[PDB]
């Protein structure tokens, strides 16, 4: 068995996403196929920010409600997706798993991981917002509703005297995924027929952030919050070339 290994990094300035790929070519002579493990890392910034003001009474906050990582082989490719990790949804604050010389580790407080229905050509992970306590008051989710206070997810005070924009929760008092962002650690295994003639493969990797629109307004007596789901989507797509002969992945 021979193992050839590599790092690839691209930063998407527009979408604020550091996209890191660690790859391993595993060539075991007693295996029917050449293996490539694509470890998908980097960081998608949260970009929790007040984006709007309209007097002292109305204000809006953009906040990340989902992160996504997807790998997709073009239609006419002979190579196939053979395995993926996590293999299923993950509910826990932390994800840790050892593959055999990898330890996958990522943190996802207030979020959970959903595995997108894999094919032989595509696989993906959604890290979606679950629920959150707000200064010991929650848990609130995207569907929380109160007849007086509306959705209170990111409402600082119910009755505060400040401008609307000064009444959103501090990102440091919430999940680190909101501000600091999300750092993926997912693994994909590609297999390739050794006898196949075109010993080159294209693969696309997509990083995605979906942001919600959390809005505060003054109800003449108190603050009221409303959330609109999936207002903005930021999609960063990248094509890599796989060369099974040379055992390189490039950019």
Image (cartoon, grey):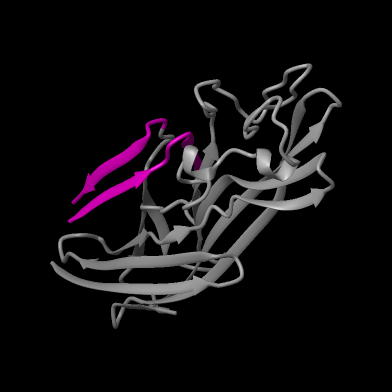
Residue at 29 percent across and 83 percent down: it is: 246
Q: Position of residue 222 (x, y in %)?
A: 77, 24
Q: Residue at x 53, y 44 (%)?
A: 171
Tell me if residue 61 is in the magenta stretch.
Answer: no
Q: Quadrant of the C terminus?
A: bottom left
In the image, 41 versus 179, the foreground residue is: 179
Q: Residue at x 75, y 33 (%)?
A: 226
Which residue extends farthest bottom? 246
Secondary structure mostly taken by the magenta-highlighted segment of the chain: strand
Based on the picture, tell me whether residue 114 belongs to the magenta stretch.
Answer: yes
Does 207 sit left or right of 196 as displayed?
right
- Nearer-the-camera pick, 113 or 196: 113
Rendered view: 18 above or below 200: above
Instruction: Provide the residue span drawn in magenta.
Output: 91-116
Tell me if 209 is positioned left or right of 37 in this view. right
| Outermost residue, top side | 147
Task: Give how far across and how far down residue 57 sits, in percent.
Answer: 82, 39
């Amino acid at each position: 068995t021979t193992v050839k290994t590599g790092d690839l990094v691209t930063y998407d300035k527009e979408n604020g996403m550091a996209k890191k790929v660690f790859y391993s070519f595993i060539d075991d002579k007693n295996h029917n196929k050449k293996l490539l493990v694509i470890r998908t890392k980097g960081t998608i910034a949260g970009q929790y920010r007040v984006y709007s003001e309209e007097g002292a009474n109305k204000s809006g906050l953009a906040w990340p409600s989902a992160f996504k990582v997807q790998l997709q082989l073009p239609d006419n490719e002979v190579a196939q997706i053979s395995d993926y990790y996590p293999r299923n949804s993950i509910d826990t604050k932390e994800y840790m798993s050892t593959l055999t010389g990898h330890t996958l580790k990522y943190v996802q407080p207030d979020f959970k991981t959903i595995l997108e229905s894999p094919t032989d050509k595509k696989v993906g992970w959604k890290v979606i917002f679950n629920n959150m306590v707000n200064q010991n008051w929650g848990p609130y989710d995207r569907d929380s509703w109160n007849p007086v206070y509306g959705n209170q997810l990111f409402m600082k005070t119910r009755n505060g005297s400040m401008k609307a924009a000064d009444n959103f929760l501090d990102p440091n008092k919430a999940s680190s995924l909101l501000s600091s962002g999300f750092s993926p650690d997912f693994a994909t295994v590609i297999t390739m027929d050794r006898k196949a003639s075109k010993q080159q493969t294209n693969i696309d990797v997509i990083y995605e952030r979906v942001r919600d629109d959390y809005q505060l307004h003054w109800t003449s007596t108190n603050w009221k919050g409303t959330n609109t789901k999936d207002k903005w989507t930021d999609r960063s797509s990248e094509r890599y070339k796989i060369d099974w002969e040379k055992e390189e992945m490039t950019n």
